[PDB]
Image (cartoon, rainbow over all chains, first blue to last red; front, side, top):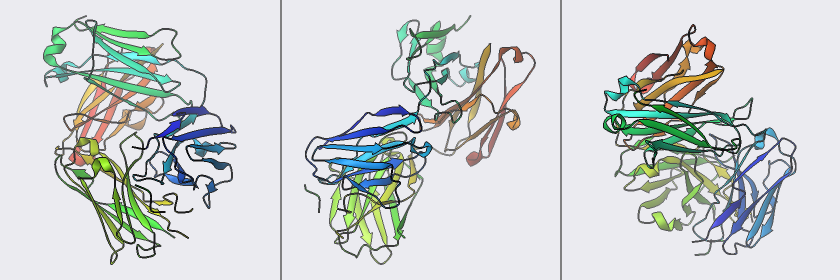
Length: 213
Length: 5
Length: 217
């Protein structure tokens, strides 16, 4: 199938910056490429159609160019309302593919996460399940890696996480990861470890607790 | 398949 | 001008069929070359093209979902319908219908989109949450784990709204059980741990379930 590759997938910038973003197509799509801006909770909004035509009503700072397999979207001066996700779409071949999107967020100085680990409550253990959670608070940039370990055994497939929207005031993100185990497995092991990897950390940091101690 | 237009 | 709005069931059972309707005004599916397509978006994922139907009943579906989708249009009601069969939790997403201009260049885009409808696929029944503490022991963190509830949404406040600074209520995750689970945390002075009290106020309107969980070391 025809693949549409968007680069970079994520990008940090400041108000007033000039940014250019690209969409690459595995095969020639002539001029049949559209660009959309999508703010969280809202539907995509058309910016450029037919690769270079500025959609009516759309601000002048937006512009697009390209043909065949290479295309770009440029924002001459970004505004606060431009911190969103951008997508390209080709309508030359069926199916009408969309790119993977480019996330543009607010840039600020690198901030390492403050990490905390929370053992499961005795109340929950009665239910037959143990949830242990790890909190990565107020960090930047967004990319962060959480690795769970139990008695030094790497856990895989039994955790879930979610991240907050970038903070309006301090531009940071926070992340919560939950490791789920049966009560039996929880009482069977001793050390519960949450290891965090992030650019603001010279080396991965590990927060832990011993179930009985 | 090519798009309609 | 042109406007579209998606309607249908916000909740659908695994294996069942999803039927969505796109009602529009400001234009008509009669007017030549005009199209109405469907695009979906899984929470936090990218846009995915589903199908499109034109004025001449011409039709196209995403290859991968072709044996599961059926798209039709009723000119008498200005509505386009999308039927997706044997849905599973991965089909949980926001479904959008959009308009495509006909030959007057401008055909190369989907110029107007609906607000989108959120569809959740779970075999789950309405259920209130269990609220567990995330106990703390300079800055200290503490919180509440709001587990196994359905459906969204749920509200969390701290100290009856008196505590707002340092609060982070995370997006809920849909577990494999089909039930949601979310956490809310707040960061505070460690010195405040022994004197100030911290209580999360949880409200799951769907189940008429309210819980006040006091959290401590």
